Image (cartoon, rainbow, N blue to C red):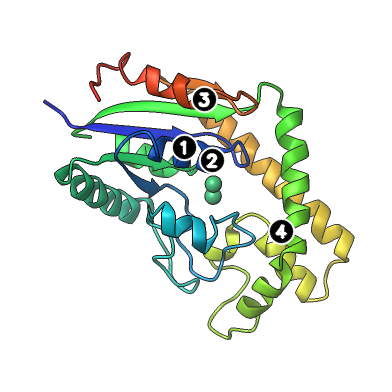
C-alpha cells in the first residue's frame, strides 16, 4: 500500500497558500513548498512569501533554504521533496505540496511511491486573476519591494543574470535601480512578467491529468477539497 500525499497547484495569485493553510487545520499535514522562488532567503516581499508569523503557525518545507547567490535544480527539488515527504509520512503526517513551479511537480511524478490527490485552484475568468496580479504587485512596492531588491543589488556576489533574480518582477526592480527604467515602466513590466508566468502555468495545467479543479472565488473550497480525497481512493 502507498502512503497518501496531496498536490495543491495553480497559477500565481490563485490563492493556493490560502487553501493549504485551511487544509492544514483540517488534517495532519506537512506543508511542502513547490516554488523555485520561495527557496531564497531575502526574497520575501516580491515573492509573496508567507509572513514570518504565518510560517510560524504554518511551517513550510523548502522555503528559505538557499542564499540568492546559489542555484537550485529540479533534481535537487526532487531529492529534497522526497526526503521531506518520507519524513512527514513516518510521522503519520500527510505531505501537502503547494506551489506553482510545474517543472518541480513534473520531476517528482516523472524525473512516486505515494497515492497522490492532485488539486488545482484558479478563477474561472482569467481577467479576475489578472486584476489581482496587478494589484498585488503594486502592494509589494508599497510594502518594501524596492528596498528588498536594493539589498540584493548592493551585493557584489549577485548580478541581474542569476537564477534567483529570475523570480518574476525582480529583474524589473533591479533595472529600475540601475537607472534603466522609470518607476512606471518597472511597474508595468513587472506585472506583464507575472501575467506571463500565469500564462505559462495555465499551459502546463491544461495538459495535466488527474486534476480536481477549484474556484478561487468559491467560499467552500475546504469541504470540497476534503471530499475529493476519497475519489482518488484515499482513506483519511
Ligand atoms: Cl509563491
Ligand atoms: Mg503562495
Mark 1 secondary-structure assignment: helix
Q: Residue 187 in the image: x percent, y percent?
A: 81, 57
Mark 3: few, some, or many residues within 10 Å (few <14, many ≥20)? some
Instruction: Identify the residue at horizontal 45%, vertical 22% (top origin).
Output: 223
Q: Residue 196 in the image: x percent, y percent?
A: 68, 42
Mark 4: few, some, or many residues within 10 Å (few <14, many ≥20)? some
Q: CA distance from mark 2 to mark 3?
A: 10 Å
Point out the frontmost of discs 2 and 4. 2
Q: Residue 85 in the image: x percent, y percent?
A: 25, 45
* Mark 2 vs 4, N-terminal side: 2
Indicate which disc residue 140 carries: 4
Point out the frontmost of discs 4 and 3. 3
Residue 214's image quarter? top right
Indicate which disc residue 221 carries: 3
Instruction: Identify the residue at horizontal 19%, vertical 46% (top origin).
Output: 86
Q: CA distance from mark 2 to mark 4?
A: 18 Å
* Mark 2 vs 3, N-terminal side: 2
On the image, numbered disc 1 is attached to which residue? 22
| The residue carrying mark 2 has its beta carbon less than 8 Å from ligand 2 | yes
Amino acid at each position: 500500500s502507498l502512503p497518501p500525499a496531496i498536490f495543491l497547484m495553480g497559477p500565481t495569485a490563485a490563492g493556493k497558500t490560502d487553501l493549504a493553510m485551511a487544509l492544514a487545520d483540517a488534517l495532519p499535514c506537512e506543508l511542502i513548498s513547490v516554488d523555485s522562488a520561495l527557496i531564497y532567503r531575502g526574497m520575501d516581499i516580491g515573492t509573496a512569501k508567507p509572513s514570518r508569523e504565518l510560517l510560524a503557525r504554518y511551517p513550510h518545507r523548502l522555503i528559505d533554504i538557499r542564499d540568492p547567490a546559489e542555484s537550485y535544480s529540479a533534481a535537487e527539488f526532487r531529492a529534497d521533496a522526497l526526503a521531506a515527504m518520507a519524513k512527514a509520512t513516518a510521522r503519520g503526517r500527510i505531505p501537502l505540496l503547494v506551489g506553482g513551479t510545474m517543472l518541480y511537480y513534473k520531476a517528482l511524478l516523472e524525473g512516486l511511491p505515494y497515492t497522490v490527490a492532485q488539486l488545482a485552484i484558479a478563477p474561472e475568468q482569467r481577467q479576475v486573476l489578472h486584476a489581482r496580479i496587478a494589484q498585488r504587485f503594486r502592494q509589494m512596492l508599497e510594502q518594501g519591494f524596492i528596498a528588498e531588491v536594493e539589498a540584493l543589488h548592493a551585493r557584489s556576489d549577485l548580478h541581474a543574470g542569476l537564477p534567483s533574480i529570475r523570480a518574476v518582477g525582480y529583474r524589473q526592480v533591479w533595472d529600475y535601480l540601475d537607472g534603466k527604467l522609470s518607476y512606471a515602466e518597472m511597474t508595468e513590466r513587472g506585472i506583464i512578467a507575472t501575467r506571463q508566468l500565469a500564462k505559462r502555468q495555465f499551459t502546463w495545467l491544461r495538459s495535466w491529468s488527474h486534476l480536481h479543479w477549484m474556484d478561487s472565488l468559491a467560499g467552500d473550497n475546504l469541504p470540497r477539497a476534503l471530499r475529493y480525497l476519497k475519489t482518488v481512493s484515499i482513506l483519511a
